[PDB]
Image (cartoon, rainbow, N blue to C red; front, side, top):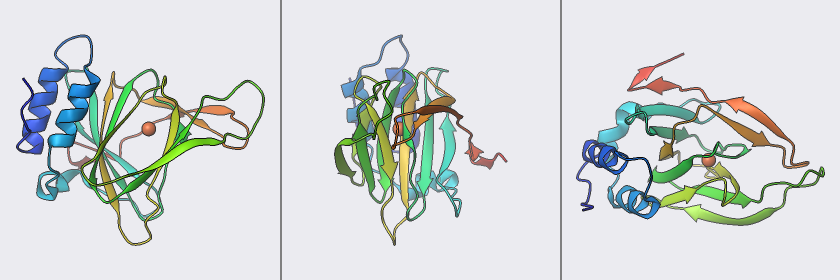
Length: 186
Ligand SMILES: [Fe+2]
């Protein structure tokens, strides 16, 4: 029985319930994430920005069944084109807007990766991606407004691939956390 999360803490409690088992009801998880109304006071602790690139701030480690983190995107900050390491990935906007661009998995041939689609993710909206859907890039294209997003990955992963848009070639990257549970982790 899915109820509206009253607070971020309440959302986290609900997520522990939704991930108690071995599988993932994606539509239910997405619905609960969307239903949480972002309250900046509840997540200010995690919203640690860096001037030069977006930061990943760990919020909850789940049951070891998911990583829940907050990403802080300065004006103009964006990600690589990347995959999600055979995991579910939910992305909910807490503040601002992000542009998501979708790409197909490349062929062996070196070739320009052409976008398949793009969309604008707005405050409180939750998006979902997995490797079967494709690859994506996420960017804060705003010149004036930082963006903050809440990401849930299951199972947790600490590596993924970045793809070179000009060729489709991939390289493995290790994800690092800017902070964990509100504590800067240099
Ligand atoms: Fe992603």
